[PDB]
Amino acid sequence: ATGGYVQQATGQASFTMYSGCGSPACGKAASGFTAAINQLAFGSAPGLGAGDACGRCFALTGNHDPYSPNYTGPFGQTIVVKVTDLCPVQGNQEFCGQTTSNPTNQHGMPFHFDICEDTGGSAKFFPSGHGALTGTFTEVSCSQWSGSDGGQLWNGACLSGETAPNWPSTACGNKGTAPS
Ligand SMILES: OC[C@H]1O[C@@H](O[C@H]2[C@H](O)[C@@H](O)[C@H](O)O[C@@H]2CO)[C@H](O)[C@@H](O)[C@@H]1O
Image (cartoon, rainbow, N blue to C red):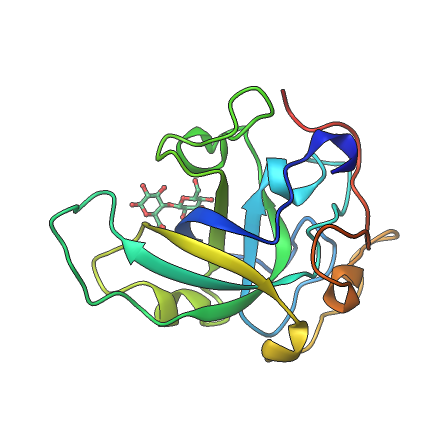
């Protein structure tokens, strides 16, 4: 996409969970299940505001524990998250280090979703004792997402991806150039 970001409506991803998504990089939180997506897919860098991932909805499915490869299941449920946040390259090399010259993370995944624990998404997705998974994602209509957006936290906050057709398309728009 514009800026060299890798923004595809379906693919393979790794998955983690994080705490504190009340002030996310898109500039609006949301009451439903939400996630951060890795910088290369988010469409912006730290401090540059919302990228074109902002507010898009994705169905996530975990099917492998890379830390416990002998574990055959059960995994969690497929959940639908709204992207509100950025998992930046800086400080997240294992999972969010995808760059245009090296587009997979240390688990070979081209995308990563960091699922917010606060609003319940990770409890539906991660079996107890299994904090990181790999699997698949598919962008879906936000008709499939339960919840309401929070208010703007600053000028330029954007979740307009929630009404956009699936990638390839433009809503909030990408900022700057993808990390190389
Ligand atoms: O770095 C992305 C993401 O990781 C989260 O911690 C992971 C950790 O990286 C992984 O090694 C462990 O097995 O599972 C935890 C939880 O999923 C961390 O909570 C996030 O803040 C961070 O953005």
